[PDB]
Length: 57
Length: 77
Ligand SMILES: CCCCCCCCCCCCCCCCCC(=O)OC[C@H](COP(=O)([O-])OCC(O)COP(=O)([O-])OC[C@@H](COC(=O)CCCCCCCCCCCCCCCCC)OC(=O)CCCCCCCCCCCCCCCCC)OC(=O)CCCCCCCCCCCCCCCCC
Ligand SMILES: CCCCCCCCCCCCCCCCCC(=O)OC[C@H](COP(=O)([O-])OCC[N+](C)(C)C)OC(=O)CCCCCCCCCCCCCCCCC
Image 1: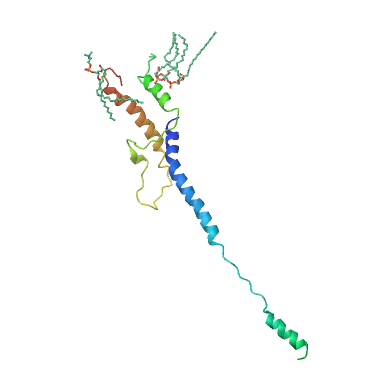
Image 2: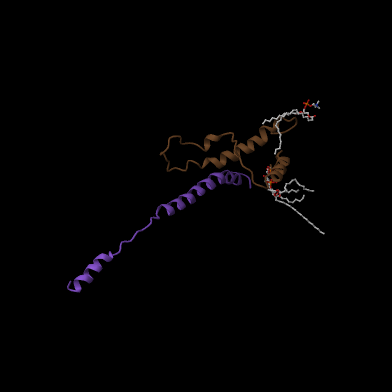
C-alpha cells in the first residue's frame, strides 16, 4: 500500500525519459537507412548504332 | 499467562491510511546505503544483495513512528 507504490512512482520519470530516447532512436535509424537509388538504363545511342549497322550502312 | 494489549500507533495508522490511499514519491531515506552497495561500475553480485531493502524500509518506518513521536509527552514506546 505504501512502499512499493512510492518506488514505482520514483521510477516513472527515468523510464519515461529512456523510452522516449529509444523511440527517437528507432525513428533516427529509420531515416538513416533511406538513400535515393538512381538506376542506369542502356544508352539509346548504342541502339541507334545497332540500327545503323543492321541497315548495312 | 496471556496479556492482551495494543500498540500506541492507532492514530498514526489512521493517518497512514488517510494520507497514503494515493501514491506519493519518496526521495529522503534515513539509511540510503541499503540501495547503493556497489560504487564501482561493471561489478555485480550473484547473491541477493538487495534483499535487505524492504526490511530496512519497514524497520525504519516502524522505529520512526515509535521513537520520534515518543518526544511528545505521555507517548509510549
Ligand atoms: C473472554 C473475554 C474475551 C477475550 C477472549 C480472548 C481469547 C484468547 C484465547 C487465547 C489466546 C492466547 C494468546 C494471546 C496472545 C496475545 C498477544 C497480544 O495481544 O499481543 C499484542 C499484539 C498487539 O498488536 P497491535 O500492534 O496492537 O495490532 C493488532 C491490532 O488488532 C491492530 O492491528 P491491525 O490494525 O494491523 O489489524 C488489521 C486491521 C486493519 O484495520 C482495520 O480493519 C480497522 C479496524 C481495527 C480493529 C482491530 C483493533 C481493535 C481495537 C480495540 C477494540 C475495538 C472495539 C471493541 C469493542 C468491544 C466492546 C465490548 O483489521 C482487523 O483488525 C480485521 C478485523 C476487523 C473487524 C471488523 C468488524 C466489523 C463488524 C461490523 C458489524 C456490523 C453489524 C451490523 C448489524 C445490523 C443489524 C440491523 O496483539 C496482536 O498482535 C494480536 C493478538 C491476538 C491473539 C489471538 C487471540 C485470539 C482471538 C480472540 C478473539 C476474541 C473474540 C471475541 C470477543 C467478544 C467480545 C468480548
Ligand atoms: C523533521 C523534524 C520535525 C521537527 C518538528 C518540530 C516541532 C516544533 C513544535 C513547537 C512546540 C509545539 C507545542 C505544542 C503544544 C501542544 C499542547 C500542549 O500542551 O503540549 C505540551 C506538551 C508537553 O509540554 P509540558 O511538558 O510543558 O506539559 C506540561 C503538562 N504537565 C504540567 C501536566 C506535565 O508539549 C510537547 O510535548 C511538545 C513537544 C514537541 C516535540 C517535537 C515532536 C516532533 C515529532 C512528532 C511529529 C508529528 C508530526 C505528525 C504529522 C503527520 C504524520 C503522518
